[PDB]
Length: 178
RNA sequence: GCCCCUAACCCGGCCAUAGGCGCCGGUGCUACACCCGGUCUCAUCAGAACCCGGAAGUUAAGGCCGGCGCCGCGCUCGGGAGUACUGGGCUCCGCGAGGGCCCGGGAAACCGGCGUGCUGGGAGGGGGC
Image 1 (cartoon, rainbow, N blue to C red):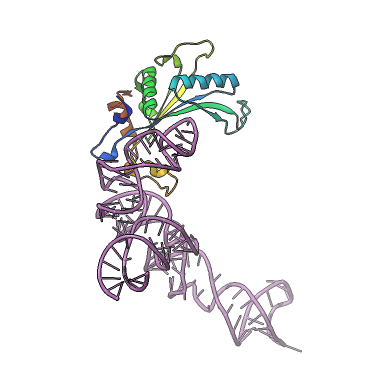
Image 2: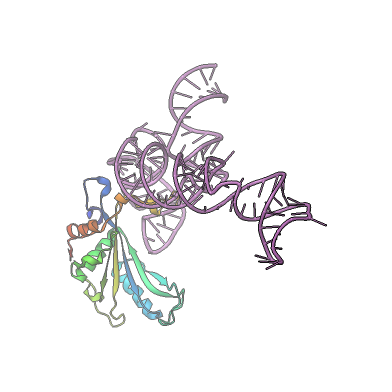
């Protein structure tokens, strides 16, 4: 069960749905060492290099200034995305709320503690963290919106719907959607 | 070479009649695409993008063309209207602020009507020299 054949296929070859990407986010308050622990935890958990996310706006109630890094997120595609997606679904319990699916092929779920993931051991030097995991599904032709030259809008029939995303998650990933 | 005719492609001009929303179609040899990969040039958290190498698949989408409705927009169109306003003259009216007459110019909102890109150069294709 790999990425290239994790596709949901309709009666047209060009309307195949697939996992465009999986993004894992840890949002921590400010800490230098706390953020380094979060970044290392994301690196070990996903196998990919995390990217530090700087605060967009200074909010003094949270004690964060604009430009300082308070997030650690990693974008996973193809094989690493599928492997971590299976691990994270096992951690959550193979269950996703139907109301968690937005109307455009995006589904995000939270992992409260990362020890629930398979293959992870409690460490006192790292503590216990949570994550947001967001899966973005797509059809072929999405590059028309993202390319540099002649960028245009993708037509409505070629965009992933909420019903198609829920059907993909049930029939292809074998997750229980309620 | 050179002349003529001509889709989608490339470089433009004016920059909505060109935009927005929704619905119905056409187009696929070639061209434009979606597309397939990441050895190399190059690139990032991420070959998503950019960059490179391709050609299995598809016109589903983009692009281009045709039709309809709405919003917006445009017009040297009819009305509004010779109206509002106004250049010059006056021993002309009014207590007065002001208004009037003559000569010369003359809108706008809005209503209805119509329209909904036009066009320059090149490639490619066809017909002659």
